[PDB]
Image (cartoon, coloured by chain):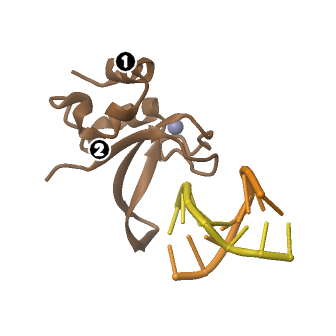
Chain colours: A brown, B yellow, C orange
Amino acid sequence: TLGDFAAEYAKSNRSTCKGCMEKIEKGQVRLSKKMVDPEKPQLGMIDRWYHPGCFVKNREELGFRPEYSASQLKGFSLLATEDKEALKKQLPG
DNA sequence: CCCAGACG
DNA sequence: CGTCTGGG
Ligand SMILES: [Zn+2]
């Protein structure tokens, strides 16, 4: 049972990192685990976003397999090479 | 004022 | 789904 993760340039300035609970700026690289919001299970499965760094603090709780690296962050390939590199560094080996 | 579309 | 607001 793999977690389903995603990467992308934030679509707007109105989402909030789940790790630090700070607002993510439009345009910034952001990672998501799609899952159920505790306080809103009514919604069911939804995107929960993270600053890449904050995402990594919680790599384990989130269900990230360092064995598969970045391939499991659906949409990685769409990112600029610059960004694809920076990201790949932080991800645990 | 409006409302698509982002978010939770 | 209801809410909010960026960009008309
Ligand atoms: Zn954060």
For residue A23, which quarter of the picture?
top right
Position of residue A25 relative to residue A66, above or below, is below
Residue named by callout 2: A61
Q: Chain of mark 2?
A: A
For residue B5, which quarter of the picture?
bottom right
Position of residue A25 relative to residue A44, above or below, is above
Whether label 1 lies within 8 Å of ligand 1 gets the answer: no
- The front one of A62 and A5 is A5
Determine whether the residue tagged by mark 1 lies in a helix, strand or loop: helix
Residue plotted at (40% across, 20% down): A81
Residue plotted at (22% across, 28% down): A69
Coordinates of residue A92 in the picture (x, y in percent): 26, 23
Residue kind at label 1, given as amino acid type? Glu
Q: Earlier in the sequence, mark 2 or mark 1?
A: 2
Determine whether the residue tagged by mark 2 lies in a helix, strand or loop: helix
Residue plotted at (32% across, 22% down): A88
Coordinates of residue A63 in the picture (x, y in percent): 24, 44
Residue kind at label 2, given as amino acid type? Glu
Residue plotted at (37% across, 18% down): A85
- The front one of A41 and A83 is A83
Left or right position of B5 against A40 = right
Instruction: Quadrant for the C terminus of chain A, please.
Output: top left
For residue B1, which quarter of the picture?
bottom right
Q: Residues within 10 Å of mark 1 (few under 14, many from 20)?
A: few
Q: Chain of mark 1?
A: A
Residue named by callout 1: A85
